[PDB]
Image (cartoon, rainbow, N blue to C red; front, side, top):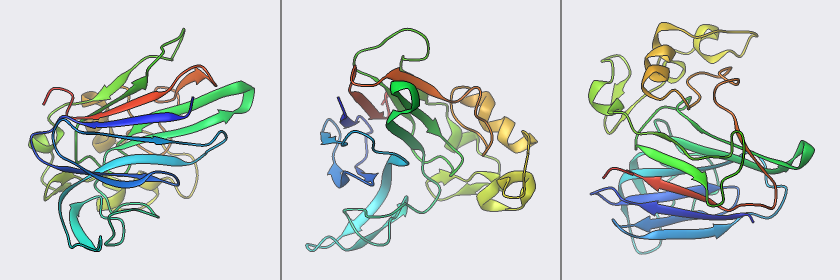
Length: 208
């Protein structure tokens, strides 16, 4: 319960990050990072940072997902960064989790329970070649930004009230049907498992 394995299967190095628990860890291909989240942990995210350069003290910078120039993240990363989000022991004894591209996409990833269950408690992924097919307007080095990051505004960010899918969010949704494509993409993007029944695993580049 509450245990996360973050495994890197990408050809390149990935500096894993996680908040509010976890921190960060350099992961060469084949390596795993294990951390535990106390029961009740909410608004948590796990992500990978690419093309980093750190000194001996842990200060540096990353091309994507940079969390304030430090290796062990205390805060969120700079988009674009594919996200695995979770909240344990929420209402009705359920863990709520998802993969999100609301803050862009940088690395393909899978996210799922170690002990599956009925309903939505099964593994999901977002492994489409988003970086290679990314629209020119959203394209950045090593990633593909969500229109809310690139353009801003209610239409894409939904800060002013109800919003719906846009041509750009749909572009993401077509490639990753199980991931959050825009702020209010809730019905087809939320997955759950009964609390205290399973651990979780995140993999960067499942297919290599």
